[PDB]
């Protein structure tokens, strides 16, 4: 089967460089052009770079020309993207792709995530979203604030509570740190007797927090 | 030189129903048009190329048509995985590949008003000099919703951020969190914190509030 496998993603500081790699298998790598297409968080697809079958021709998007270099090594069935002078707006998932005729992106890799930021790794503070305790439905949650980089995971009661949970996408603050909330709806009659604990894990910082959330005095 | 426009940007349709998506090119691209599907959390895949040809292995429910500037993608019966984002694509002048901005196909359902909850900052957070006030809009449909923050009746603009979940796998609703950020010093200068929500399911806006300290 046609397969493309990317590697080399990560967190990089603005102005620095990163090289992405994409290895093909299951087809004749040298026959056709190769491409990189990226998707910034929450945005659409943007073609970045193209290289002809034998590397004799390279094309780039205007946003990326001069700073990025596409290259290939057909003897290793690999195509590369060398990303220099990285800018915050280069943060995206980068997909490698291959073509049959040059018109279209017939096959796609799995993506490599590139995050461009001057923020330092930092685990979150976890604050309670305490239930009001005032249909008999209450809401409670955890505010997972000021962490970098993504991702964080949140469970409730160590996985024993899944119904009614909503863990929201993180927002990026102007500080460069992320914040997100995780909430759950539960019966208000349970608030005095049932313990609710959010389990937060931020693996990049080796930060794990279990926060019990209860009605405030 | 060539712009692809996908409109409408969101289609709300029922499971098992027919869908037709539109791509319009600003000038003719003849039949050199492709469509991609991006399923939730997955890479894009090619569905249709040369306007009407199905890529190898693609299910027979996908079809396409058009020539010149007006193109369509048809899904004869929407399967669960087809609630996805679809992009059209063209290539001009041999060296420029461009995409439309995408159309999201979402699950249509009956209108549901949000249940609304407001959360004060915790005392623990206030120790560090910042206050986060959170408003939750739970399990609503359709997606369009407006949150307005007020602090002692002063409308807040510019100092909040919102996030929305993907459509729920069981009830096809959305939920939304809005966080108002203030300094501790400012938080302690005011009494009434309110989140006002406007939604098609509400006959009039709903406000949830608290009085600091009470």
Image (cartoon, rainbow, N blue to C red):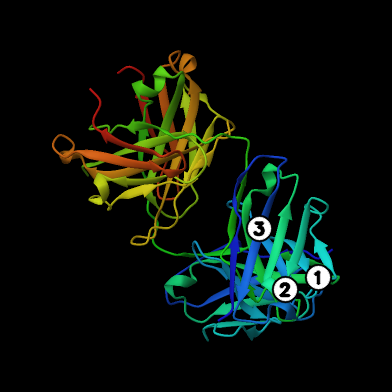
Badge 3 vs badge 2, beta-carbon distance below 8 Å: no
Q: Which residue is mark 3?
A: A20
Report the chain holding disc 2: A
Dot 1 crowding, Cα within 10 Å, few <14, some 14–19, many 20+: some
Would you say the residues marked 1 and 3 are in contact, meaning their CB atoms lie under 8 Å apart? no
Q: Which picture quadrant has residue A103?
A: bottom right
The numbered mark, 3 or 2, whose residue comes first in the sequence reads 3
Instruction: Indicate which disc, 1 or 2, sits on the residue closer to the N terminus.
Output: 1
Decide which of A58, B25 is in the foreground and name it. A58
Mark seen at residue A74: 2
State the image coordinates of residue B68 (x, y, percent, origin top left).
Answer: 78, 78
Residue at the image point whose x is 84% and y is 72% from the top: B94
> Rounded to the nearest whole Å, what is the CA distance between mark 1 and mark 2?
9 Å
Q: Secondary structure at mark 3?
A: strand
For residue A90, the mark is none
Where residue B148 appears, as percent x and y from the top left, is 49, 34
- Residue on which disc 1 sits: A55
**From the viewer's perspective, is residue B25 above or below residue B190?**
below
Query: Total label count?
Result: 3
Question: Mark 2: which secondary structure?
Answer: helix
Discs 1 and 3 carry the same chain letter: yes
């Amino acid at each position: 089967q046609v397969q493309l496998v990317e590697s080399g993603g990560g967190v990089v500081q603005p102005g620095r460089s990163l090289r992405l790699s994409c290895v093909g298998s299951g087809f004749t790598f040298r026959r056709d052009a190769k491409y990189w297409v990226r998707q910034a968080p929450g945005k659409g697809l943007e073609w970045v770079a193209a290289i002809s079958h034998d590397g004799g021709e390279e094309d780039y998007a205007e946003s990326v020309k001069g700073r990025f270099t596409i290259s290939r090594d057909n003897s290793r069935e690999t195509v590369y993207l060398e990303m220099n002078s990285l800018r915050p707006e280069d943060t995206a998932v980068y997909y490698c792709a291959t073509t049959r005729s040059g018109w279209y992106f017939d096959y796609w890799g799995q993506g490599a995530l590139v995050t461009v930021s001057s923020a330092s790794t930092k685990g979150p503070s976890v604050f309670p979203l305490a239930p009001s305790s005032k249909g008999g439905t209450a809401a409670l949650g955890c505010l997972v604030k000021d962490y970098f980089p993504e991702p964080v995971t949140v469970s409730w009661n160590s996985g024993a509570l899944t119904s009614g949970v909503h863990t929201f996408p993180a927002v990026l603050q102007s500080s460069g740190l992320y914040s997100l909330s995780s909430v759950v709806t539960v019966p208000s009659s349970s608030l005095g007797t049932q313990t609710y604990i959010c389990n937060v894990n931020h693996k990049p910082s080796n930060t794990k927090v279990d926060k019990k959330v209860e009605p405030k005095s | 030189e060539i712009v692809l426009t996908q409109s409408p940007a969101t289609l709300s349709l029922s499971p098992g129903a027919r869908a037709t998506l539109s791509c319009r090119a600003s000038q003719s691209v003849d039949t050199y048009l492709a469509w991609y599907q991006q399923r939730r959390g997955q890479s894009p895949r090619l569905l249709i190329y040369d306007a009407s040809k199905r890529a190898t292995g693609i299910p027979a429910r996908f079809s396409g048509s058009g020539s010149g500037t007006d193109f369509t993608l048809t899904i004869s019966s929407l399967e669960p995985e087809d609630f996805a984002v679809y992009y059209c694509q063209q290539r001009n002048n041999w060296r420029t590949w461009t995409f439309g901005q995408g159309t999201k196909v979402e699950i249509n359902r009956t209108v549901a008003a949000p249940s609304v909850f407001i959360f004060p900052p915790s005392d623990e957070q206030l120790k560090s000099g910042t206050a986060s006030v959170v408003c939750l809009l739970n399990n609503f449909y359709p997606r369009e919703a407006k949150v307005q923050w007020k602090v002692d009746n002063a409308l807040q603009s510019g100092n909040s951020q919102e996030s929305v979940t993907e459509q729920d796998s069981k009830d096809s609703t959305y939920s939304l969190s809005s966080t108002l950020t203030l300094s501790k010093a400012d938080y302690e200068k005011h009494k009434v914190y309110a989140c006002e929500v406007t939604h098609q399911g509400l006959s009039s806006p709903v406000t949830k509030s608290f009085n600091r300290g009470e």
